[PDB]
Amino acid sequence: KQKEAIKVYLELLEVHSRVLKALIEQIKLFIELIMEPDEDLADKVRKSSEELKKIIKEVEKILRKVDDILEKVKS
Amino acid sequence: SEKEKVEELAQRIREQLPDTELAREAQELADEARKSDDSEALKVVYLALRIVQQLPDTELAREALELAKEAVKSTDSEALKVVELALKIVQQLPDTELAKEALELAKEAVKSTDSEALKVVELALEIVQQLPDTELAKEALKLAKEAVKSTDSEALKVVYLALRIVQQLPDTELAREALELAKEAVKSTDSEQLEVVRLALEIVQLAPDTRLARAALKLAKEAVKSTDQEELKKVKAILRVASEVLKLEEEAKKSQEEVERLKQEVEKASKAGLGDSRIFKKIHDVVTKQIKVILRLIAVYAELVAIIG
Amino acid sequence: SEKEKVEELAQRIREQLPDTELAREAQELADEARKSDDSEALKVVYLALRIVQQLPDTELAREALELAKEAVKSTDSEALKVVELALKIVQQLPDTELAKEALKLAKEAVKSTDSEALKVVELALEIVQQLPDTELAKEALELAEEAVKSTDSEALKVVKLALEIVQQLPDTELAREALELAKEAVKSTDSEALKVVYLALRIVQQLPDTELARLALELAKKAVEMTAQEVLEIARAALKAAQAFPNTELAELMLRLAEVAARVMKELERNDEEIKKDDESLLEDIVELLKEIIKLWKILVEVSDVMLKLIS
């Protein structure tokens, strides 16, 4: 019912806070790369991108859970 | 009681060296102070007479008397505080070049009508007082003396920010880098370099002891060294974007704290049963704020993209 | 020379309809034009009198006489050209709503002394003359009317750019979309929407016949549809990024990212509407929001990779 939407919104809030942190790191590193080109800075930017991809995977898991619940409701 | 102290020092000075120019000037200054009801001017005159009693028949005492008279003439409280700090520096560090330089800087500050030069000179004097016998004090005093001469207000703001950075983190690489950058910016006649240095110093103050701060300092140094105008505008835009990113980071941290508190409150309300519609409304408010912060971050991302191209 | 033509038309009109208000107005206009030595004022009075001779005792002739008098009062060459084009349109499409609305717009332009409004109205009249008896001419005329009525300085420039786009690519999907977008922007009271629409139209004109132009048109339409200022700020940032870096795959990805973010905000609004009131519909809207969220983050990852390739 509504508690399911509540828990989905909570999961989204936590994921989006982690997104905020990763995005701030990514923008800081991009400014640093613009001002000075380095290879290790590019490596840590790639690490940030990997973190963002893991976040995307978590969002996909949330979506598949909600989809299973919707498919059970429609039955 | 301050009037009593001033008059007692006046009588002590009159008994110390009568029939001298310093004695007559001290008597007249003590009279003009007794006429006053302002305690700050009373402290000014007290420090002046204390310096006179400290060094009788000297040039420093004459400078102190003249500066104290000109400060009593002024109605601005900031000039009063500046003269107080200058005379107090002369008292704390006698027989030092910094005392004479600070007296000259305080005279130049009182003579100026601008309100920002008073703050700048007060900051320089506080730097001298808190860090005596240090290169930072002399460099800050020289920087303030150079800032008073410049016509541009941007130079005043830049030197204010540089002295602030020095006071916040003394004996750090950031402080000496900010001092050198502010000196080289005051030397340059260009105002765009002043804007770049101001933005870099603001980046430093917003995020002290961070990688962004030192990176922006190095970029501002190499931009002051450079002579390309397009790269100068690009550096200005990059520094503005960095400052916006710092502000957005603060906002995002506040939003994350809100998210944690909302999760706690949601679990508490689910345990208690206090109903679901109000919880959904609070969740909607928090989601709105967080997603607006995310969208601002995306906009800054696209702005950076436009800058690099 | 031209005075001869004007005075002959005046005497012929006097012989055609005596003891009428139109006769007195035409004679006064002819006398005032005869006193004037300017060639353009003489040509405008000639057109007005020829219109009076073509449509005697009609409202169009009265409005043309009044417009000719007001143009004689004005010294701006652009306003004179506007009045001349309006009268030539009246002659070109007699007894049409386009001619009446064009006379009205010409009067509204003459009233204002600003040069940008005169240029916009001249552009609209050139559109009407170039495409007579077409819906695009009607839309451009109404858009210019709405622009002149608006006090915002950006609205005039936006409408001028839209009309330039229409003239450059007539009877195209891009021109129709630009007309509708400019109309919706003038309808909007927000200035951020006007700036976003100007950026979109500038992207269309600066790079026609490209996917980025269509993307910018879609993004600007969806931004004007939304009432949120944040979506407009995102659209403005994305359009500035696209304008600064054209003919690139990364700008395409950036416009796509902005569109996905606008769709995410739309799904947020839908979720709010459903909260204000079924569980199944709420779950479906949550599913759609999660889909668009995943797309947004994927596009952000792609943008990050492309920027890393550009900086390395």
Image (spheres, coloured by chain):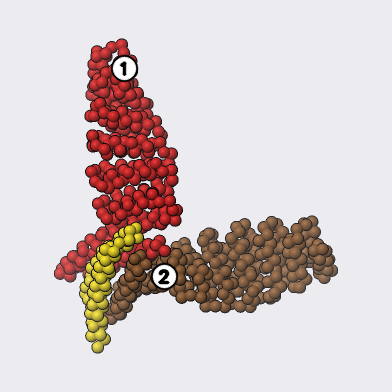
User: Residue B136 in the image: x percent, y percent?
Assistant: 27, 39
User: Residue B243 in the image: x percent, y percent?
Assistant: 33, 55
Residue at point 30% right, 38% down?
Answer: B139
Query: Of the residues tagged 1 and 2, which is closer to the observer?
Result: 2
In the rendered structure, the colour chosen for chain A is: yellow
Q: Which chain is red?
A: B
Chain on which label 2 sits? C
Quadrant, the N terminus of chain C: bottom right
Residues packed near mark 1 inside 10 Å, few (<14), some (14 to 19) or many (20 plus): many
Dot 1: what SS?
Answer: helix
Q: Which residue is mark 2?
A: C251
Left or right: residue C247 compared with residue C70: left
1 and 2 marks in contact (CB < 8 Å): no
Q: Which residue is mark 1?
A: B22
Residue at point 27% right, 47% down?
Answer: B174
Amino acid type of the residue tagged 2 in the rendering = Ala
Residues packed near mark 2 inside 10 Å, few (<14), some (14 to 19) or many (20 plus): many
Residue at point 56% right, 75% down?
Answer: C169
In the rendered structure, the colour chosen for chain C is: brown
Identify whether C7 is placed above or below C267. above
Depth order, front residue of B13/B208? B208
Q: From where the camera sits, is residue B5 visible?
A: yes
- Disc number placed over residue C74 in the picture, else none: none
Cα–Cα span, label 1 and label 2: 77 Å
Residue at point 60% right, 74% down?
Answer: C137
User: Residue C180 in the image: x percent, y percent?
Assistant: 51, 73
Amino acid type of the residue tagged 1 in the rendering = Leu
Identify whether C267 is placed above or below B295. below
Chain on which label 1 sits? B
Depth order, front residue of A9/B30? B30
Left or right: residue B74 compared with residue A50: right
